[PDB]
Structures are given as structure tokens and as C-alpha cells.
Length: 241
RNA sequence: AUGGACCGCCAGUGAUAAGUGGAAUGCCAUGUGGGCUGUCGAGCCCCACGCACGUGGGG
Picture 1 (cartoon, rainbow, N blue to C red):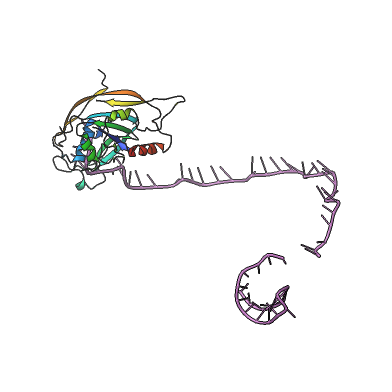
Picture 2 (tube, rainbow, N blue to C red):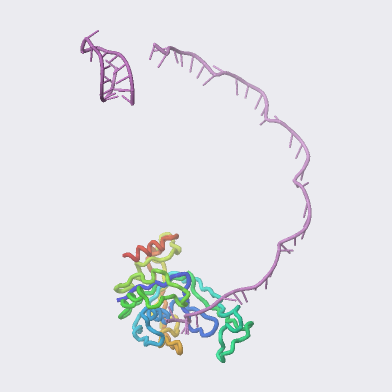
């Protein structure tokens, strides 16, 4: 069982621990987000039991860490006072203060290839191919790369993360081999953060911590693609086989 | 349906005024393009004539 999910695209955000106007992303995908991505693909209404998703495992290798950028993002500004965001008391604030100013962060030009291994993950892959709601990378405005699922069915996909999945253009030294790539596994634990989603109900979303261990591993330098456009070519060669 | 869903950074604005690149200056001195030379028998068809050697008409 298992399939390869490729998270790529111009921008993707995987925030955790932010609860005000400023938003912040983890430099790598968060299990909560990917689980919600599958739940959205399967029609799981907000508030439905998320234990079906329990028992999955997410090893994620970071091809390009990507640049982290902060996207300004106002809400309601430049509108007449009557048509701005409501207050909790119900009376709209004065128009010179009715604007909301959020500073949301997002990863741009970053690409990870998570190898999801679970009990029903093959039905989940078959659900991403025909989604109930549009899958997106973190914020809904970010739209996933068309090669969202590199392979629908793979026996031992981590074995395919160690090798035989192409890689972006990187420095390849003379007489070099085995270019270093950071794999992320789920003592030797990088960080602890609230990921595993106890409930997605918008009224009270709650989570619990998951330790992450990031192990730099060594994959053959043959894997990295040539400088220009070759990455797309090798990747497409990869999807048909 | 993902610390997410819904979500504008935005309303305004001459870069202006002034200005010779200017004065002087031979690319000069030398060189065969030469020897040779009369312009004097397939061709595909139709038709007419023929002394079946050959003539002519048309395409």
C-alpha cells in the first residue's frame, strides 16, 4: 500500500500555531493540512470523525526548501462604512478603522514529495484523482501542481523516495555522486508541534503534538535533473512509468 | 474542505530651468596581361506525292 503525493506549485502555506492577523507557515508540510486535504478530497464535512485518517505515515523529502515570503492581505478596506466587516457587537467600525490587516506567510518555489503509507491510502489516492472539493496547498488560493499524485499505487514508496524519483537542478560536483537530500520522518526528534487533527470543526478545531525527525540522507546524484526544463521532462517520463 | 474557509493597501502628484566640442593637416613614390586559334546525318504522329531513292504539307 501507499502512494506518492507531490506538493508543488508556485506557493503553498502550511501554517501551525497562529491565531491572529499574522499567519506563519512551517517550512515543511504539516500532517493536519495533508489530512484535511484528503478529507476535502473525500467529502469529509467539517466536524466529521477524523480517525479514518489516523494510522497514516508521512515521510517527506524536501527537494527545494523554497523561499518563505510574507503576503500582505487586507480585508474590507476601501468600502463604505455600512459594507465593511461586521463587529461582534454587530455595529460596523468607523471606515478609517474598518480595514483588517493580515500578514500571511507562504512558501514559494518549494517542492516536497511526501510518501504517504497507510491502510486505505490507495482509496485516498483514488479520491484525489476525482475530488469532492478542490485540493489546495494550505491556503485555498494556492492551487496544486497538476502532478499531485506521482504514482497512485506503490509498494513501499519510501524506497522510491530514496531513489528513482527525479530531482530539481542542484550543484553536481565533478566525480560526485549521492547528492544530499533531507527526508522527514514521523531522542532524535527535530521538533514537536500540534498536527494530528482531533477535529476539523470550525467551532473548535483541536490538535495534538507529533515529533518530527529530519534525517539528511544521501541519494544518487544521477537523480537530479539537468539545468533547464529537464526537471519537467524527467518528471513526466516518471509519471508514465 | 488543510491555524484553515470568506478576504483589494488605497485614494493624490511637471523633474524642473540654462549650454560651440573647438582650433591644424598631400597617402605619397614605382609598373606589358602577356604569348596560341577556319564555326564548317533517329526525330514521335497524321495527310498528300513518289521513279519507295526519296519531296512536301501540317501538328
